[PDB]
Each structure stands twice: as structure tokens, then as C-alpha cells.
Image 1 (cartoon, rainbow, N blue to C red):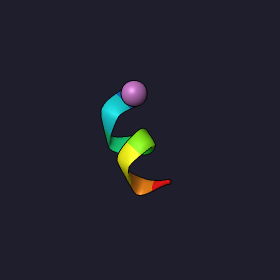
Image 2: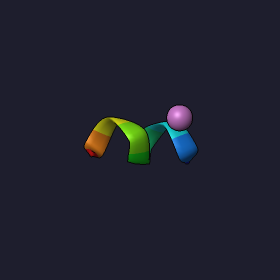
Image 3: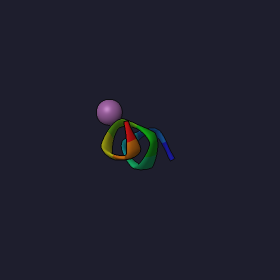
Image 4: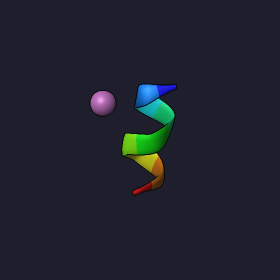
Length: 9
Ligand SMILES: [Pb+2]
């Protein structure tokens, strides 16, 4: 979940 968000941003 944390990774997904870092990538998105
Ligand atoms: Pb991250």
C-alpha cells in the first residue's frame, strides 16, 4: 500500500 502511493506521487 505504502509503495503504491509513493509510486503514484
Ligand atoms: Pb515508500
